[PDB]
Image: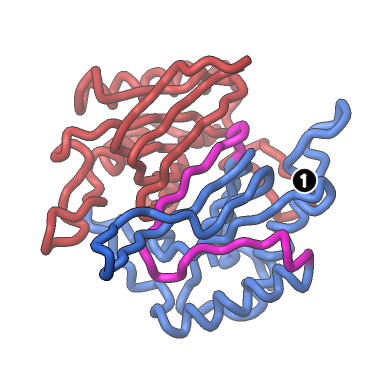
Chain colours: A blue, B red
Amino acid sequence: MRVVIQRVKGAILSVRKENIGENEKELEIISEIKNGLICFLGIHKNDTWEDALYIIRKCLNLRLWNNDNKTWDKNVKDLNYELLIVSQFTLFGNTKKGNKPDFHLAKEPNEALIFYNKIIDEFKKQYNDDKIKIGKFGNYMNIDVTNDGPVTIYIDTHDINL
Amino acid sequence: MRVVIQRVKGAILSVRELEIISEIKNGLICFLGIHKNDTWEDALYIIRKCLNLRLWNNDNKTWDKNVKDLNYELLIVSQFTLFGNTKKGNKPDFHLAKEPNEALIFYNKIIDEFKKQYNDDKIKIGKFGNYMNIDVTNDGPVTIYIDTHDIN
């Protein structure tokens, strides 16, 4: 599994919404957080539950907020902050050969959805049902993010021995 | 070198009462991490990939158009935290990251090469080594990661 974690003062996620209908075609906000993390999550085809757990553990526990003259001190749970988890297959975009990304390492959308939903449940079980927002899996999204720092963290779980 | 590329409809960068100092419409924001043992070859790979990755649909085709074809912009932000090791604790430690003073020179060389390889007016930057607030409109999203240490 791969994840890119961004520290944020807020994030607003929107998808396309077509009233077919009333011939209305606009963006509508379906998810929103204030301070916290946005995590772009890429799932590898050979990912196991252990990979998910490491990611969840790291996202929930990384001390990324300063605190009273102490830096890199507080985690997203401590400050009672939120997480926005977006599935992001492009993180398994191989750009090593040619300038068209190739996504053969990506888990296929269907198995991915089940896995992803398992992850979201675990996030909630390990933190709080109300602190975890998500996007619209497999749909085009517009995400207004306020990067606070910025602080960007990258983790590839296939780097660790689990 | 490590880079995270985000596809965007726009980005607004401010620095500390904040003031906006950089702004782009459609294009890419690129968070750039420089490794202590990085060479000019690593920079070139990153620059070439950023300018040439076909990340836009030109319709009926996918992954078809790149950032130059569309006359789009790039916002390059140095981002040492990309070398935050988190393998051994919950507190990132950043020793793979290049020392600040050498990093700045290197980083400025990169920005020049970006301009030389594209266009002086299409390349925006942040305030190196300063706290920044960046409002980004992610378009997709489309997130690309590259570690030039994976390549020879």
| A147 drawn magenta | yes
Q: Is residue B81 above or below residue A17?
A: above
Q: Amino acid at mark 1?
A: Arg
Question: How many discs mark residues in the rendered view?
Answer: 1
Viewer can see residue B83: no
Quadrant (top left/top right/bottom left/bottom right) for the C terminus of chain A: bottom right
* Residue A55 appears left or right of A72: left
* Residue A11 appears left or right of A25: right
Compare residues A6 and A101 and report the one nearer the observer. A6
Compare residues B135 and B88 and report the one nearer the observer. B135
Region rendered in magenta: A127-151
Q: Is residue B72 above or below residue B49?
A: above
Task: Name the subunit of mark 1.
Answer: A
| B151 drawn magenta | no
Which residue is located at x 11 percent, y 63 percent? Answer: B60
What x and y, as percent, mark residue A51?
Answer: 62, 72
What x and y, as percent, mark residue A53?
Answer: 69, 71
Compare residues B21 and B81 and report the one nearer the observer. B21
Residue topped by disc 1: A63
